[PDB]
Image (spheres, coloured by chain):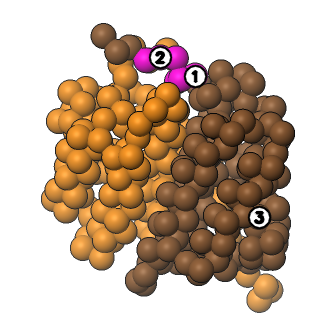
Chain colours: A orange, B brown
Amino acid sequence: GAVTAVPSVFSSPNLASGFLQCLTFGIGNSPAFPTQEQQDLDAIAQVILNAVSTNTGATASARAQALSTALASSLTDLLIAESAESNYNNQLSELTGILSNCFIQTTGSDNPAFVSRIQSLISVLSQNTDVNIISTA
Amino acid sequence: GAVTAVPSVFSSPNLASGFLQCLTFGIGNSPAFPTQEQQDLDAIAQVILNAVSTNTGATASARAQALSTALASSLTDLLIAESAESNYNNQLSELTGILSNCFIQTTGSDNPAFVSRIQSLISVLSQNTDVNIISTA
């Protein structure tokens, strides 16, 4: 552990715009992301970055961290659900690429912390595929 | 093994707002949350409820699910960061209660899925330290 690279995006409203406008271009550019599914991705993503646009104060650091995981959490949870539960990895490969690429373009780095948060969330999110609770049997 | 019921709070912007109207009072009435930390929590929480409020479309159902995870994620992440990643357990015990209590009042249920998601996210939030990996150089 111990990350030696801090993502300044979530700590700067100006960078939030750049990252947001990168997402809306990347997600709509990848072959794995269809138009109606892009709707939700872009919509949820813009909310997180807008929360960065209102970051100011001593708690901005904590907010940045929270938004970092919140972004990964919401996007991944949404994606998994509408990707046939099992086939979510098909688009996840592209999603992670876009995210990391946008970090490169916006904060000038990859930020290993973000992707680490993602991998951690994926495990617990996909864990809830026990939806065989159908009371038909 | 349990029939999953969907909380109407994530399907109704009027309830989403009401849920926030509970959080703002509950957090500010808990002896583990300072007046400053409270207002920050409220500020982060409202972001998710505003996303619930913007639930419109075919995939709004899945958004409700993702936002559920995002709410648990962001609030806990914010909390852990400002509590040295070790003292979070003190305030975590109150936060988790407030959330469920607000679900009880707003949507009329404990929401077993939400609390389970919280604990699952604890397993990943408390699996790595990120609040002091900052390298602003």
Q: Left or right: where does residue A98 sit relative to residue B107?
A: left
Type of amino acid at the residue the image marks with label 2: Ile
Label 2 crowd (10 A; few <14 / some 14-19 / many >=20) = some
| Location of residue A129 by image quarter | bottom right
Magenta region, main secondary structure: loop
The one nearer the camera, A70 or B37, is B37
Residue topped by disc 1? B129
Kind of element beneath mark 2? loop
Residue furthest to the front in view is: B35
| Marks 3, 2 in one chain | yes
Q: Does the residue at mark 1 contact the one at mark 3 (Cβ under 8 Å)? A: no
Say whether disc 3 or disc 2 marks the residue closer to the N-terminus. Answer: 3
Against B36, is B26 above or below? below
Label 3 crowd (10 A; few <14 / some 14-19 / many >=20) = many
Give me the residue at 81% from left, 32% from top.
Answer: B90
| Location of residue A128 by image quarter | bottom right
Which disc is residue B133 wearing?
2
Q: Does the residue at mark 1 contact the one at mark 2 (Cβ under 8 Å)? A: yes
Residue A52 falls within the magenta-colored stretch:
no
Chain on which label 2 sits:
B
Instruction: Give how far apart the Cα atoms at labels 3 and 2 are.
Output: 34 Å
Give me the residue at 43% from left, 81% from top.
Answer: B56
| Marks 1, 2 in one chain | yes
Type of amino acid at the residue the image marks with label 3: Cys
Q: Left or right: where does residue A24 sit relative to residue A125?
A: left
Residue topped by disc 3? B102
Q: Disc 1 vs disc 3: which is toward the camera?
A: 3
| Location of residue A45 by image quarter | bottom left
Q: Is residue A97 visible?
A: no
- Which range of residues does the magenta coloring cover? B129-134
